[PDB]
Length: 35
Image (tube, rainbow, N blue to C red; front, side, top):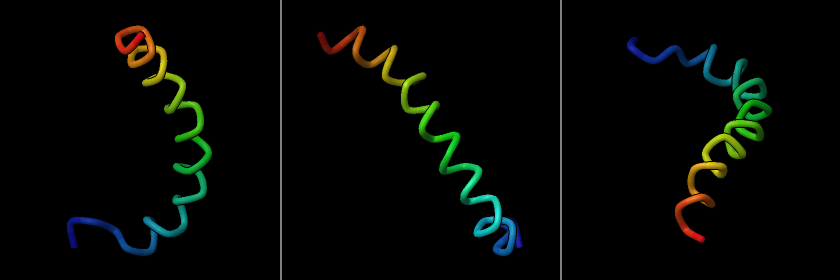
């Protein structure tokens, strides 16, 4: 059980919200290259 199944679904919402900010973090790099 390398990946935790219960935790995956539970913390999913937290990861979802953080993916919003992580998007901009990656975007700052990507948009600085592909411009």
